[PDB]
Image 1 (cartoon, rainbow, N blue to C red):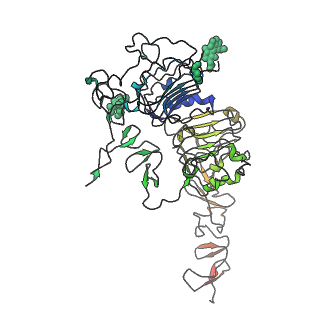
Image 2: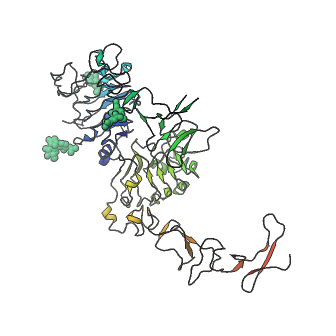
Image 3: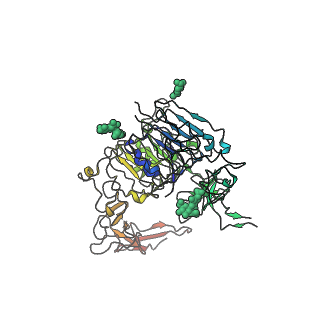
Length: 592
Ligand SMILES: *[C@@H]1O[C@H](CO)[C@@H](O[C@@H]2O[C@H](CO)[C@@H](O)[C@H](O)[C@H]2NC(C)=O)[C@H](O)[C@H]1NC(C)=O
Ligand SMILES: *[C@@H]1O[C@H](CO)[C@@H](O[C@@H]2O[C@H](CO)[C@@H](O)[C@H](O)[C@H]2NC(C)=O)[C@H](O)[C@H]1NC(C)=O
Ligand SMILES: *[C@@H]1O[C@H](CO)[C@@H](O)[C@H](O)[C@H]1NC(C)=O
């Protein structure tokens, strides 16, 4: 697309360096607006970072830390809004880009960045870096962001070449005549916050953010608040106008844009904003057909199951013996599930018992997670993720490290067993360091994804061709070779009939055990009082009334194990007394 979602990993090491770059690539390739924080970290010496080259806007902060690359190609980046700040104060943080000694970041080259709405700048520990002190920062910082901290270290093990002669003022982002700083704040006339030149004819509209092509609200380089189809405006048009009526111009706010409709995986509020999370004392209602909306509860909200990151589990790290039981009977969890080594080791200092595999069945009910699933430890006695057999959707409205809606890491599992998983609402799946794990590639991951930024990243599992030579392959009854584990329960779809959750070639219509009838490709058992037929069907439905014939006795039209002796109909005093015919037909007893 063009709008994408950033991350939230701060300075923490990537779990998967073998995969980190792929991740950055899948998140940012083609992306123009990052909603969230743009965090580029631990990029090695030779990485290609060219998938960053379309980024024109960061809504949160931008963090460039712990890389060895010499160049970070962000020359189209126009604005960092700073709706979130690093260390709660910096819109731009460039940290520790060096090697343990020549490598390390050399120039920032942010030659399009003409706007920082909120927060300041931190540049520290970057020993090859030049030109960090030749930016006029206060031109960059919005007029009312002028007191933003500038904490810019210039300790260097190299000599900086000057700003190229062609630079009209002595300001630049780098040594080349292309990296000249373009000034759009400090050079303006009067009460003009942003301009394209020194004259008032060059003033930008007040609703523009980084600069302009001309004077109009259709000529902005970026919108200060909201882009309403090519016009920057203070507000999106209301959904309702005042008698009060519906407004056919109505728009929803999504980021710095006015949208006709909320994007996938988002909820609509009455006031027409889009959220990942409802305001307090709301409920999520699924319009019958796809939509979800936030609606305030007139009386007390129905009791709901909160997972990690949410309400009283806001600060909780992991599912544990002290908390598993809060999930009994839960179909929907608002929040996330994470199972870490601590979950299964316990902690003898708090007295926390290790989580027993049996306790995990409290999840057999689970159909939906609004946040993420993160599994970093799992019992060795559980060969698969079968306790989540009925899990249908991981929404990924909250994501681990702000990137992953499904993580399985360093586990001993042999198969997945996630047999109901049909949807990863957003975020990436990361499945790595599971040395005995097969049936990863038998899953049709493209079918669970919902945007083109999502992918499965994988490494260190069992090679697929090594599984495929040991008979760990999809059962042959699974349609299209798609399955989640070995055997006939693990199909994504059955090509034939299902008996319970087992895929079978045939129902027991003529042959078999207890006899069966068919209904919607489903093997269903005849009543136990039906007599199995040697030649024909044994039943045509489930009830005692629906047998070819009775194994024991018959009462009116249904096959029965015993004749009624003294059975009283609901609201009657008169009991029925019967006895079986010589041919097994229940007849009325001659006495009451
Ligand atoms: C990144 O680039 C450099 C430069 O090509 C790599 O260093 C080279 O290593 C190869 C392989 O042995 C040598 O043949 C070159 O002569 C080296 N060049 C240098 C720096 O003098 C470096 O290994 C690369 N780093 C990564 C992350 O692979
Ligand atoms: C505001 O958003 C509009 C989208 O409505 C952007 O304008 C479109 O940009 C695409 C790709 O850049 C063009 O192909 C279309 O011709 C444009 N359409 C419209 C509605 O003008 C626009 O760039 C954004 N403006 C700002 C200031 O960010
Ligand atoms: C950079 O140099 C000065 C003076 O030599 C020193 O006091 C300062 O602490 C250094 N910066 C860092 C990385 O601490």
